[PDB]
Length: 299
Length: 299
Image (cartoon, rainbow over all chains, first blue to last red; front, side, top):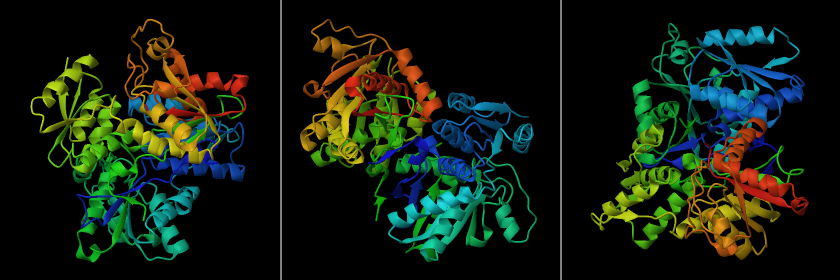
């Protein structure tokens, strides 16, 4: 019966856990996206972007994946390329975690060394163009199969596990696919007018500055996985009800609290997402509303 | 609806994935116990041992857990003590991973430094006896709630997800609870005469030497999580059909293969368990039999 044909098909069905030391009488529940292959939410889009390029015939036997590693998107693509027998080439800067090196190289990846993150993007492109018929780039910030997998899985899991009671969905934005696809699932396919809340670093609040017509001022920050410093094409502004900003220290402190007080290990961007939800959760406005927060990764 | 009241209740329902480059035409399927809170199988027993001591009244508000950290059992207990509001004290040797230190201390654990693993056991005991009314020791190698949680969850998940077709269950033995409880579920509660296969390091094959009446010769090895060098009280010899030995290098190489060829990240003890299953899987004897292998952890 329920035996997945490869590890890519095992993505998702991640759990909902109620928070005890956050929110107001249990109105904050978290979706633990770390209970995933490759230990992050990115497994969903790594699988679906590979899957869709197969349906497209833009990806076939003997074609080699190339992608600019967005830390976690590289691991997810790596494990999927290995699960489906594709050669893969990832590009990311000159250092990062030497654990991420050993892991990617352990996953059978061919890794490419560039000199920042806009810089790594380049050497992927000149590698793709080095031979356009051997190489496919998936482009995670604009590939519609990124939000589409969330509209098809992440959103519906939230709908089913909350029996339709979900009132607010809180999610940080890196590529924007999670909140776009979730919000699309619940508003458009299920028909409930929830409050979609994007979270971004207060140190780089380009979504807030954009929507307010203010000067867009990207800046350095420590909240890994969100705050790309621009509006991704996979972030559908038309569906964002509200934007919440969080600073790195609060985002970190919140991650520590989730561990010590809830027994939940999550990355700093989950701490940012929880801090934002807790803020909403303690407005009387949201006192009797079920808030669901995405925890995108483990650590 | 499906919202867990704390992280301890979210244990389990881990997935089955068919292996492509192991076994004979798909007869090896793996159970990814790393898709668990705390990223290992031990989450199941950390929860259930805490839960059962609560039912017992051997553990109540204000009592402080003490336990000799078996690497992964410490992390699982840590996250459960935090999820249920217990103070916890774990004992393990003088070094290990300074990441495990930061994680345990991050999980709110009070950590105790001893000078080997039989040595760490001692300072827990003299801490418990330092005040028997404040401290509870759970004793993972002999506590029946360890195999009992596998008879209640792990076994039945295997039964349901294979629609009863599971013929062989392959599992490494540290405390012995996984294979005991699984085998008890399938043989005794469901009534199928499967082949229960224990895996142990060839460098320390005390189960094989015992069952053969030979000299029991424990020895050093690198397969972390199994091979305690003795017969645990939670390992029910009466239910073991077969014992398979695996060396550290093969166990490691197999873990690498699972990553590079299957896209599955698992620890070295999962590599040992897969190597053993692959051996069985390529006996004509087992050619038309579904083999389920426990992958106990991520890394």
